[PDB]
Image (cartoon, rainbow, N blue to C red; front, side):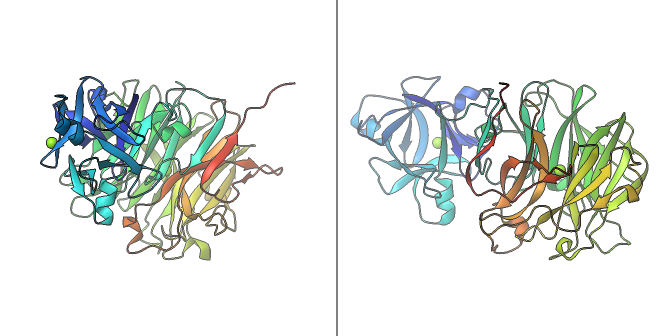
Length: 472
Ligand SMILES: [Mg+2]
Ligand SMILES: [Mg+2]
């Protein structure tokens, strides 16, 4: 039939897999073939829509329910087996663009996971529906290992991932890290194209500690390659105060960061101890800098933007320098904050975008600009644009855009902004616990005056970001 992976809708790092003939959803599936299935015409009925789910490694073995529990079992040729191993593929119960699997012999019951085990249950609640919805990733899906010089995406590229960091490495892959909705782990994925980030198999490369430091909220990881090694800069609270957040570093010298060993290097200390988050790094003219957000107890803002020179990838040196603090009304809706700095170099300037206001629909982006020949450690080299440079747009239906990163087309010729936003405005409850910020991308245009034009957040759907020009 058709080889496929079956990815969970609500745990999109997790896949239906053979676990020594038991059946569960897991991340980090090893061997990868445990998550590979062949969708074949239904054993009990080969009509349109009916399928059976066969193991690739164990041909003749299929997913079969018994007492509402799933096992991977050898087809015994009986009618009861065929019926217990046949499903109708129907529009996803939680989202009709995804897939749900309705039992052939129990048509009110669907394949679902609970406590990570695969079951066949009736589906009542909104959570039941999410547990019963899956993404089929098959040969028709974008292949993350295939190169393409054109950049065409379908937004949202990655649902339910916030603070998206995309890094184009010198192996022909983009690497993506992001905040996950539970804020409890660091997830990494790679693809040769931006659109393939949607279908790439992520890996959980690190999970939070059970006690003490690095045991609270895990926020906004960024992967960088510096001096021949991989680094992840991330923000982590403690187990007794999820918001007592500091910067931490992981290091991996193995060349493939999805298979390599990651080592904790500890806290990246700054000039004082307080809420510190959202670090990024850039190099210019032989100096490396850290740029991050931090609370100053003496200033009534949740965080300000700081820069400092680095002494290698693990430390700053000298004094940190505040280059932005929230002061315009648009930086203070809900609360006064500047966070999520991202660096873009062009046209003789260093541009740093940042996000401001609360993380609901009011979230937006501002811009800092310095001449690239100026003293970057002098606050007066940095100039804040007086208005937001990217914000909600009711006409495109995108709300609270921010915590962006910048990458390029594969050929390096154009800049592309990757960021999160919601496709609805009103949020119920604490916005930190609304998980529906989705990762998306669009071109960065350039004004004739040399400054970036971020435009408005594009509506959901297909966006042609870049087609490479051709010499006559
Ligand atoms: Mg089972
Ligand atoms: Mg960041």
